[PDB]
Structures are given as structure tokens and as C-alpha cells.
Image (cartoon, coloured by chain):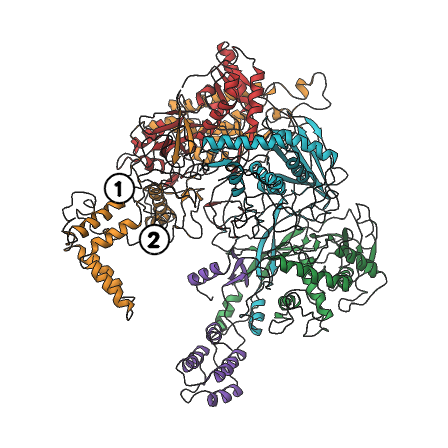
Chain colours: A red, B orange, C purple, D cyan, E green
Amino acid sequence: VTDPEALLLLPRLSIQNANAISSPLTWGFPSPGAFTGFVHALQRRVGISLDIELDGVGIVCHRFEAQISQPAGKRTKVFNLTRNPLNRDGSTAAIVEEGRAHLEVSLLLGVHGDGLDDHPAQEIARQVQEQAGAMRLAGGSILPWCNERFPAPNAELLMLGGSDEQRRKNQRRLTRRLLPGFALVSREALLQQHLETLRTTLPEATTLDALLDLCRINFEPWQVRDKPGWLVPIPAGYNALSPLYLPGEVRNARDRETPLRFVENLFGLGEWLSPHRVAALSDLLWYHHAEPDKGLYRWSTPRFV
Amino acid sequence: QELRQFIESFIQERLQGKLDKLHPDEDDKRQTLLATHRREAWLADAARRVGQLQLVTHTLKPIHPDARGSNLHSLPQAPGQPGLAGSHELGDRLVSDVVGNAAALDVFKFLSLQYQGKNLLNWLTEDSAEAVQALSDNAEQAREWRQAFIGITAVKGAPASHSLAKQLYFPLPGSGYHLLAPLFPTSLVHHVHALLREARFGDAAKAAREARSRQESWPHGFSEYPNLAIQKFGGTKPQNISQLNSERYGENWLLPSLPPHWQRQDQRAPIRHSSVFEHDFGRSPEVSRLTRTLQRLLAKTRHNNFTIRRYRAQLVGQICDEALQYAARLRELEPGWSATPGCQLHDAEQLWLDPLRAQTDETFLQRRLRGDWPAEVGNRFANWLNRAVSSDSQILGSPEAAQWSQELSKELTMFKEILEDERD
Amino acid sequence: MKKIEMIEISQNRQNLTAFLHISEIKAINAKLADGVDVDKKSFDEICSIVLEQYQAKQISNKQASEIFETLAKANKSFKIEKFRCSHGYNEIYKYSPDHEAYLFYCKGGQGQLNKLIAENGRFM
Amino acid sequence: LSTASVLAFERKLDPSDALMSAGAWAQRDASQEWPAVTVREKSVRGTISNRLKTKDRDPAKLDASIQSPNLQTVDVANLPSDADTLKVRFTLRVLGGAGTPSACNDAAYRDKLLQTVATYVNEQGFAELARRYAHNLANARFLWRNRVGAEAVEVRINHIRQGEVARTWRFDALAIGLRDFKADAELDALAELIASGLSGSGHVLLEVVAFARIGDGQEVFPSQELILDKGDKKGQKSKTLYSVRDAAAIHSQKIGNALRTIDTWYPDEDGLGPIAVEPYGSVTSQGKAYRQPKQKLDFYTLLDNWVLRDEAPAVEQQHYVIANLIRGGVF
Amino acid sequence: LSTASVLAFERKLDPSDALMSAGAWAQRDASQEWPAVTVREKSVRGTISNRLKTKDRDPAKLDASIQSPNLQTVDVANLPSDADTLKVRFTLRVLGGAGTPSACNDAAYRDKLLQTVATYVNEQGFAELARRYAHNLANARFLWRNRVGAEAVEVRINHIRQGEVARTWRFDALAIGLRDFKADAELDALAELIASGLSGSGHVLLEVVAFARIGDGQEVFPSQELILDKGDKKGQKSKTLYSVRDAAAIHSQKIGNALRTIDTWYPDEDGLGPIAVEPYGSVTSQGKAYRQPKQKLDFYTLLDNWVLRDEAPAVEQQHYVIANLIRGGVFGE
């Protein structure tokens, strides 16, 4: 929740065969929890040796192509699958449906540690950029740069050092390389007040969500209502439905050192706003905070406006 | 008393269905079994059906088709911060999809009629007013009926996951992790699926289609959901969990959450005379839809001002952002920008969508190759703002039109200051 | 000749009237039983009464084979099957009358074909 | 000790999609501007040539069923009528740290697995497995049906470090056999590069281009797609090809499966050739499965009797087990 | 021993899309800069000419349906008014390795299938099939309806070795027949080349160019496409033609059918022209089926009578079985 000292920009990042579905009720862009977990894994790989911290992300989505098809005059979509290898016999028995997507994302990470205190500026960015090219960001591999016009522009932009007009010039210089993207930010307060708006009959949050992202057509007693923005439903963290357990208690855990919980997704609201329409870039960083007393394990973006 | 005065017809439904498949010796044996277990022994059949399969409210079978683990149906209630919505508060319409080990569908369909207006569907766990006299037998039959009716919410007890069941790691602030194993919210998924079905096609859906098409007009909360994908569970044989019925063949469909430009690519203003020579064009398909939306309800009223304070400037901001996004998308994947046949106006007015430096540049190439400012861009933006909104000679009688004009002038000045730094 | 083959020959061909030439009825009315004379009768009625006289065992099997093969060669008009599967290629095409051709419908073997046949009906 | 109930290995050596473009054989070196091969739609009409049933083939019924032919609209990818060769380009990154499990339930079994894998790496280095991967990078197996009938298939693979070509190569894919693995000096240098990448240092990065002189406007074959619901209307489409940005491409797992056909130690045959490395090695083209649990030569029992009971297998089967760990899986 | 549950052959004779351009005769040697035959879109007005089924055969209903015409907008392809010959160009590559399946279930079946095909090949090679394919190349049958009424067809068959044309053939397609497969002194080199390509020795890729002198500004017939004509407006597209990058063309499988129209061994009549090598050899024009499976002369009977039961057919029918293996598909289930 701490404001960072620096916004280390990860560049144009083509990632292929991602997870499109990412939630039991959405199918579009992958979850932002994947991005916060990706930054925490990158921290566990490079930041302990670099003596820094890495907390937030800026999810911009320069381009996005799903592996879908619109089957033969229908208003829906279906998912392109992949043929799996055979069983002990030649059955092709099980076909579980999971989607894929190719997205060119570019993250901006909030640094906390000894960035300029004990280390240089370009070398830390070079190390983290050549470290993030040997891992996967959403369920699919991070494709490297082999095409022409070799960028490598890991801008390790300092934020708290400099005058105010120079700082605003640095923000509007970093926003120049976010040129065709679209930042994703949570709008929990917007969903709350939109729930209080239509609380006349029954104020269910899952009904205010499922009647806002659509196009609600309603004539004159002949129009559609004015689109307030690019509102999407996103997974906004998990919610436990079973108490805490011991490490070696629950059968077939991923590891027997950390406790287990049986959880369930929470569906929040999100917007794809242009990066020019934010004051500072550090306003749109995704952090995941947890309250282990109750069951809420929520990722969100504080200071989103 | 919903055990003999009310459950008699429910028990005799089975003894009437056992008369349809009537045989000489096997039919008499089936009728004898139905008479032994349906005259007073309904508690024993209810105990067998309760022992047969488990009751799930969120089952983790749908995440891997060959994953045999624990699927607990606990309450997902999360009363915390006011920004989260999930399966935590259903209350009504919380259909418990019992799909653990369903080999006989008549297990859960034994006492599904005495709860609609009776006190036995809630007395099927504790406080047995008719729990001892419903069977009408001794303590053995009533005890078997009670132990079977408790098994509709009796979990396995020992928690268990699988190696194919999506166990992730959540990091705490300065502590050890918590491993989270999400399960598939079957009751919530079928609640939202019933919402989508009864909003997409049905009875009031077709009537609302008629109220949209013809002269008859009834505006209400009917909508069309675009771009929703289909994810099928089970495939050819959907027996993962129940509620995958005959037209619900794993057919859980997913709400659209795609990116802002999650469609394909398209443009019409390339480096040419018909594309870039047009010094004031200002067009796009998505920007055209946004302009039609912003120009449809293009008034400034007094009772509509409480929403038109933001719904009018929001459209102009979206139009400016769409123009900036089109200008950024045009000059990124088209390196051709130089002298050529039909590229005269693509050097002065094309200061925004202009290419990089050339191969035969001169010494003072900061004016004849790429001027360091959007010199023709500001007048073009002013003309586009004047043409997109038909301002009249009485459009400043109050501050409603003049405020939009001042906002358009400020947005044009901001876009000019942004585009001035483009050539550097 | 088999027995369900005669049932499918009864089931699949078009219902025609006055299709029996003089030699066929001349052989048939003396060949079949003394019950019904088949003059200007539809194919379904003749085939149903001959299959019934084959069921309630009065006439032999070789006579029924000859007369059902005679009803096979006397008719050249077939009903359209609405669903034709490509077996090795594992596909299912569906008849579209305005194209007079079998347009593609779905990937599927014989079980999917029988499912579609049970749903939509086996003929056009 | 018992087997870990959650065992999984990340995929090493994952390739990108293999995008296809087209141009002449003379300008194969100035080929960064070659136009892509788009997929197009074309309608095909056919009679019944299937092996129809042994009962419903009556004389008049076949002539009645032949009068109505079956129609469809397939997708095709053809070279343009001036271009002569097909260029297939992808980027393969070899991650490294092969035997490290992504998820391991037991800790002692994890330590024993790491000790067994380090024992294998110390005893015999990765030169054999990296040579068998350098063969599939060298002879262009990754163009599956675009290879047969071409008169000149040659690959240009360059290892890049930080955005610049650090070491380049050139092979002749028709001269190198698809059947037998026989070495060469440049193949051993490339195998040393791949084996140094497969050690736990970090990813090594190759750009793999393959030019096949397939013909002057012929048909090229990118990978198809599973849809599993073609639609309920008139206008379905039987064959649909794969495209990324209107360029016909080969799937990434298709390229991975072409890179993984290295094992020739399966017991049932000795002249078929290598199959892909898979637990219970099952060719999807043939439709059967070698290395079944009837014999004791699958991956699962091999791993169990190698790391638990310390019963070290034959050197071919140890090569197979470590190639299966390089491939990755979920157990 | 039974047939395999999967057994599939690739096609060993691959043509491209035969794309057509236009020009003037006697300048057809310097004919690599000819303009393409573009597919224009004209408007037709048809009238009722189908058979009435004595329900609308009334004096007033026919007069009421005559006055309501059938307006359509069809594609059309024509030569320009200054061009009087049609040049149709494609490339055919002969792969070879004919009887080797691409995906076979059983090994004991495919080994003896390879044994029977090898016994055929070393007993009597692909020279008969290559002679008939070289006749369907020299006699320009791949111009399907662009050949009827043409004044003079002329085919040029190169042999593109490595970009360089190694060998050239020039045939007068109307001098040699379309029915009788007689041998020529020049055609035997092309038949030897296709036999060497099918037998495995070498890579054979030919460039076939056919000039058909139609007439000044006449009509050419490219391949036609499928339309899902659900509902039509005032004038709606009722016929569209094939076009690869704004240039008319014949489909690759329609100029492949006219290459394997070699079957003249069918039992009905060998004097009514050759037909296409197909299992239950059929022609949708004639609407019948030569090689009926009630007879023992189809492909799917002679195949498993030759491989399984080892009853070797007549010498003229082994050519048909091997030619159907060259065509391809999945056999056996």
C-alpha cells in the first residue's frame, strides 16, 4: 500500500497461449491476480539478490487476440482447443475446455528497496528485463524480442527524486510509450453506488454486476442508455468457504509447509481507461492485500482516481 | 403431518411408476419392493438415497474431469468491504446441485415435495416433529431415515484436494503464504446462467422484442448480452455435477471481459493523398458510433443537467481519447513517410501521423522533413469540434453550451500541448 | 435375403400409386395370399400388408424375398435421408434442398448420426 | 518413502508459433520483408468416396445417393503465384534447470529427485538429448507436411544474446536424415549451446527460420483447429486453418511435438522411426500406444523404480526419463 | 487378418489453382505480362422455365408469375474486346511414394500392403498411369468448359528443375484425342518424367500453361463458388466465381479431376470415354455409379481382395487400385 520510489517500466511484452478464461464467469483478459502473482514470483527470483521490492503492476494491453470462433451464424463464441495425447489406448477420452489468448502487455512495477541507494539505475532494469524473459506471466510463455527495431527500453524511472514540473514531464514522457494501450483499474466504489442506485427492489451485487456491463436497451414509453465507460467484470480476489488448515493435514496439497484454504472467486468491476486520463502512473498499480482473519484475499488498485 | 397424511401420494408415485414397467415375475417383485419400501418404508429408501450421493453447493469436479477430491458445499458468505460480489449472498435461488456420486436421481427426489409449504424440508436435519412418525416404524427405520436425511449436507469430513485442482499461493503482508484451492461455484454459475437464459430468450424476451420492433413500446429491463463465450463441461457425457441437464450440457457461458480493442484491426487513413492528404478528415467506425451516441442526446436540460453534467463531457472526452488512440495506432506500424507520388499534404497536416527520419535528409530538416509542432493539427481539431456539434447563434443563452465550448477549447489546447512534444 | 432389409425397403422408398406394371400384379395377386387384391394401392399399404402376412406366419420366406425384391426393382424413387455421414473422414453432412446438395453439419461418427436421426427424424 | 502426490515439471524449450511467409529462393537472405501467406476460403464439392456400409449399397440406392453431392467451404493456404518458397519462422527459448519440479508434495522425495537428476547430469552430460533436439532443429521436422515434396529445405538458426545475433548457422534439412541421428561438427556445437542452455543458468535463445522450396504457387499446410461446436445453421466450415495476424501459422505445440520426437528406445518396433517423448508413448497419428504399463517401460514406473528403489535403468531409458522431465508434465 | 481401423494416404499429385489471364494469339510466347481475367458483376433477369407440377399450371397463375420476373446479379468472366485467347497457368508437382500410408493403425496390415504395392511396382511400374496422366496433361482437359468450341488449344509443359527450365514440351491438345489413349513420340518423355517422379527417383514439378483461342471478347468459365442463398433482395448474388487476388481461377481440385480422368477399365462400357478414378466410380453429370459394389469391381472390394485374401485382380484393374491410392483419402474402417 506504500507509494513506490520508482516505476520500473517493463516494455512491450508479447505473451502467447495465455489463459483467456481466468474466472468462472469471465472469458476476456486474464485475471489481474495473475499479474500480481507474476510480480511476486519475479520478486522471489530477482529482487532478493537485487535488494529491492516489487509490488504493483500497470496492465495496459497494447493488443489482444483470443483463440475463439463465432460458429455458423450465432451470437456467441466458442473456444479453440488443442488436441491432447492419447491414453493407454487410443481413446481421446477427456477433452477439458480451456481458452487461450495472445496479448501484448506492458507492465510498470513499483519498486521499494535500495534501487538508487546502493545500485545503479540502468543495470537493475537490464537485469530484471533479462530475468522476466525466462518465465510465464498468465499461464503462457513470454515471447522475447527477435524482430527488428530492437527496443530494450526498460525505463527505470525515478519518481520521488526531482522537481514537480520535471516529475510531471517524466510522467508524460513515460505515458508516451503507453501509446495504444489501455490501463485496467478497479471501480469498486462505482459498483457500490450503482448498487445503491437500483436498490429499489433487491440490492444484490451479482445482479448490479450482471446488469451494468451489458447494453440495457429500453425505449421511450427508442434508445439505449448512455455508455458511462468501458466497464468489464473482473475477478477481484478469492473468498474462503472453509476454515484454515494445518500444512500436513489436508490430503494432496501443493506443498506441506503452508496452510490450505478452500476459496471462491469474487467478481469486481474494472475499466480500461487511456493512460493519458490518469494524473500519475503510480495511481494505477495493482496490489493484493489479504485479511486472514476473515476469508477475503482481495487484489485491487488503491488510489485509482 | 407430512409423513403419511401428505407423503402418501409422494410414496405412491413410485408404486405407480413401478406399474408401467410390469412383467410376470420381475414386475411383481418390483411392485413388492415398492410396496415394502413405499407403504411405510419410505424412511429406508430415503436412507439409501442419502447414503448414495453427497450434496454439493460448490463442487471442484468441473475444474478437471478426472479429479476426485473434496467438494464442500459451505456458505461462501463474505460480509466485508463494499466492492466485492460473488456467491456469498444468494439466499433465494441457491439451488444446491448435488453431483457428488449421483448414480440414482431419485435419492434427492424423495422429500422434495414436503418442503413446499411444510416443516419437514427444514426438519430434515433436526427438530424432528414428524421424523419419528413419518416412517411410522420402530427406532431402526426412523434412525435410518434420519441418518440418510442428514447425509444431504453431510460432508466427507476429511478435506482433500487433487494434483489437478488449481492450488495457488497468496502472499500475506510480511508473513507466510496461504495456499488457496478454489472450487467451481456451481450454484452461483447456474444462478447467473438462469439470469442469462431468462434475459436472452424466453417469454418476456420475445414480447420485449415485439415492443422494440413495432409501434407498441414498453421500456423495461431487457437486454442483449454480446460476445459471451461458451465453455462446455464434460463434453459428450455431461455427468460432472448435476444441474447439467438435457439442454445444459456443460453449457456454462461466460460474460465478456475483453480488452478495450479486443476486436480485429482496421483503418482507412494511410500515408497517401486519399488517406493522409485530407488535412481535416476526423473519422473512424468506433469513433463514429461514439459520436452518434454523443450527438443523439445532445441537449442541455434542467432536470437532465444532474446527469448531463458528466454524461455530456464524458462523450467529448471519449471522442478525444478515441482520436488520440487512432492517431497512436496509425503511426506505429506504417514506416512509409517520405517524398513519394501522392504525399504532398502528408507532411504539413501529417505532423501527427508522420514517419521517422529519412535517408536523404538535409541539414535544416526540422521544417521540410518533420516540423517540430502540430502546426495544422489545432485548426483541424477545432474544425472537427465545430462539425461534430452543430452550434447555432443561440447556443450560449445559458452556460450549458458555453461550458461545453470552453471544455472543447481546453481539450483542444491540451491535445495541442501533447502533440507539440510528438516531434521530439 | 434378410428380414429387416424388407422392413427398410418398406420404410425408405417414396409412396407411389399406379407403379405396378401388368406382369408384376399378374405374378403378385396369384403369388400372395387370397386376402387382399392390390390394385391402385400405395407402396406403404402393400408393403405393410405383405410384412404383416410375413409376421403372422402364413406365407413362406422365399416368396416374401421374391416379392420384396420385386417391390424393390419396381421402384426407382427414394426419399432423401437428411443426414449423410462420411465414415473414414468422420463427418456428417445435412441435406439442404435449395442447394440440392448435402452441406456440412458436424464432426461425428455413427453415434452422433444416430443421435441426430433420433432428434430430427431419419428422412426429409 | 512414498511418491509425492503432487508432481509437476515446467515445460523447458518452449517454441513460439511458426509464422509463414513466401518469397523467391534467390532473395532468401533479404527475407525480413516477405509477405505473409493469408488463409482463404474455397468451396469443395465431392461425391461419396467413403467406405459405405456392407448393407446399404443397393444398385439404385447408390445412384440415387450419388446425384446429390456433399458441399463444404474449406480453408486453403497457397503460396502466391510469383513466390516459390515458404519461410517458416519461430523463436525457441530453452529455459534450463530441467529436473527441478514446479510442484512437489514430499520434501524428501524432492531432495532425492534432485540428487538423482544431478547424478545423471554429472555422469553423462546433456550432449545426447541436446544432439537429438539439435537434429529436429537441423532437419526441419517442424514443418510437418510442408517438408515432403520440397526440393530444398534449409534452416538458418541464430542464437541471440541481448537483441543481436551472437552465433549463426546454416543446415541442409534434406541432407540430414529424418530417420537416423548421425552427428556433425556444427550439430555438436549447437548441441553444446542447447546443453549449456538446459543447465540451470538461464534461458538461451534461438531464432529458427526454415525455407522450403515447395513450388511456384503450391499449397502450404498450417495447423488446423478444434472447435467442437461448428454451429447449428447451414453455413458451417469443415477445415479451418490457424492465423495470428492474418498470417497462416503452425501451432506452438505442433512445433514442440516435432521437436520432441527423439526417443527411439520403445520396445515394440525397430524400423518405424522416432516417436514423440510421452508417458506411455502414444503416437496420435498411428492411434496406438507403445511403452504401456503391461511392460515395465513407461515413464511413471521408470521414475518410481529409479528414484525410490535406486534401481538404475538402462542408459536409453534414463535418456527417455530425463527427456520426459525436459518435456514437462503433471503427475 | 482384417483391414486397419485407420489408414490414410496423402495425394501424390498436387496441382495449384489454375489461374487464368487473357491476351492475343500468336504473341503467346512473350506472354508473362498478360492482364488477368477479372471477374465482373453483371445483372441478369431470368424468367420462369422450370417444370410446373400441375398445381400452378393454371391460365391465371402462370400469367401472374410471368409478370413477376427473377432479377439476379451474377458474377461473370469475359476476355477483353482486344484479346482472343485464354492462358490458364498452374504448377503440378508429383510427389511419389504412392502406396505408403500416412497414418496406419496396424503394422501387419501395412507391411503386406507395402509388399503388394511393391510387387505391383517392380512387376509393372507406374508407366501406364503416368502415360494416362501425361495424356490428361497434353490433351488439355483441365480447361473444362473453356475447351468446348475453342479453335486451337496449345499446351506448354515446362520442367522447373531448380528455377531453371530443364525440359520443354509443346502439345496441340486438339490434335491428340480426348478419348483414345494413343502413344506419341514426344509424350513418352513426359510420361517417363511422371513415372520417375511417382517411382521416387527425383523431384518432378511441371508448369502447365494452356492457351485456348476462344474468340474476341468471349466468355471464359472459371471455377464457381458456394453461396448460402437464404434470402434474396431486389437483386441478390446468385452466382459467384473463384478469384485468387482479383484474378479468375479454376479450383485446384477441379483441375485435379481432369488429370485423373484415366479410368477406362470400368465394366459398363470402355467406349464411352474415361471417367475419374473414384471408389464406386461415379459421375454426377450422368448421375450413376460405374463399379457398383453389387459387382465385385469397386475399389473397396478389390483392395481387400488383393491385400487380405491375395486374389490378385486383372492387370487392367491393378492400375485402377494403384491410381486410387495415388488419389488419396482414408481407406479402411
The answer to whether B5 is drawn above or below residue D187 in the figure is below
Residue denoted by label 2: B103
Single out the residue that lies furthest toward the top.
Answer: A163
The residue at 27%/43% (across/down) is B153
The residue at 58%/53% (across/down) is D73
Circles 1 and 2 in contact, beta carbons < 8 Å: no
Q: Whole-Å distance between the Cαs marked 1 and 2?
A: 27 Å
Image quadrant in which you'd find residue A249:
top left
Q: Classify mark 2: residues with Cα within 10 Å, few (<14), some (14-19) or many (20+).
A: few
Comparing D45 with D2, the one in front is D2
Comparing C120 with D308, the one in front is D308
Image quarter hosting the N terminus of chain D? top left
The x and y percentages for residue D173 are: 72, 42
The x and y percentages for residue E213 are: 77, 59
Single out the residue that lies furthest toward the right.
Answer: E185
Give the chain letter at badge 1.
Answer: B
Residue denoted by label 1: B92
Q: SS at mark 2?
A: loop
The answer to whether D264 is drawn above or below residue C79 in the figure is above
Give the chain letter at badge 2.
Answer: B
Q: Is residue D249 visible?
A: yes
The answer to whether A132 is drawn above or below residue E133 in the figure is above
The amino acid type of the residue labelled 1 equals Asp
**Marker disc for residue B38:** none
Image quadrant in which you'd find residue D259:
top right
The answer to whether C54 is drawn above or below residue B43 in the figure is below
Q: Answer with mark 1 or mark 2, whichever residue precedes in sequence.
A: 1
Q: Classify mark 1: residues with Cα within 10 Å, few (<14), some (14-19) or many (20+).
A: few
